[PDB]
Image 1: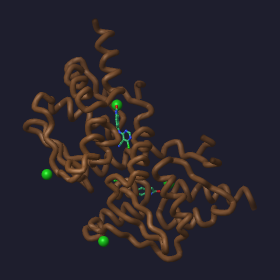
Image 2 (image 1 turned 120 degrees about the vertical axis):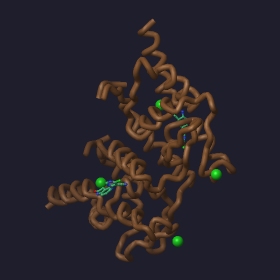
Image 3 (image 1 turned 135 degrees about the horizontal axis):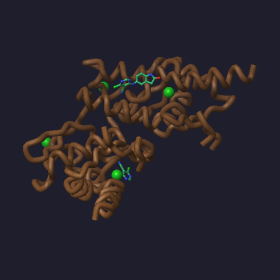
Image 4 (image 1 turned 90 degrees about the vertical axis):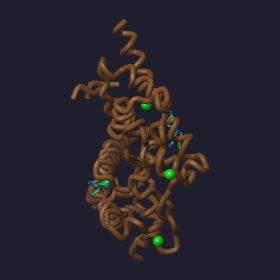
Length: 4
Length: 4
Length: 124
Length: 124
Ligand SMILES: N#Cc1c(Cl)ncnc1Nc1ccc2c(c1)CC(=O)N2
Ligand SMILES: N#Cc1c(Cl)ncnc1Nc1ccc2c(c1)CC(=O)N2
Ligand SMILES: [Cl-]
Ligand SMILES: [Cl-]
Ligand SMILES: [Cl-]
Ligand SMILES: [Cl-]
């Protein structure tokens, strides 16, 4: 999971 | 395009 | 093999599947979550959820145009997860995390359940 | 928005769509290319090809279960492109590049046409  |  | 790969292909396919969903193009099922209804593509649902994969591979349920979810399922939680299926983006907030996690457990979406558990553990 | 994103989601959806295709699960059209037939999902074809997007948004053609391609289309070229649609991987070889490029032009798959033009220009 990432900060897009 | 890339070499996978 | 000796194939070349187009990095953005999978993302572009998903963007178009979401565009088709928004325009109600070739949607083949309606998911009913208490008073709310959500139109979708069976193949996208199966590709994202262990529960839908099970349902639409069933010899009788594969032909249904309406699927009614358990009455305990929160429509907002389902809406957030349906958006995630079509976009890779999860709108996870303090006010919805419990509903999102419960819905992801029911839908059998392991990666979502995992990030919800981690975000909850960080706040305790 | 304040969303989080699962990097591998789009790739995992596509992998599952390919698995469904291989098992002939919820495939809803057969593409006929001279003596050869290819089963697929209309939504994936539309999401990858300008030609299929046009065909399946047509009020009459959207309901067809069989689509016959132009007799000049090479089945191997179509097979290579269908695999690319479901995998992001293009099996581009000296022996098939002309057929692949012609098929990609017909199917309106701009990124494929682009790499074919570049590979051809490098060999001249
Ligand atoms: N459609 C399809 C499909 C196929 Cl073909 N093969 C394997 N899994 C498929 N889908 C599916 C099954 C289980 C789970 C998910 C998706 C996400 C998750 O957390 N569990
Ligand atoms: N399905 C869908 C779709 C939608 Cl909804 N919106 C926009 N394009 C869509 N698909 C589509 C149209 C034109 C081309 C491609 C795909 C690849 C390419 O080279 N040209
Ligand atoms: Cl029904
Ligand atoms: Cl997931
Ligand atoms: Cl027909
Ligand atoms: Cl393309």
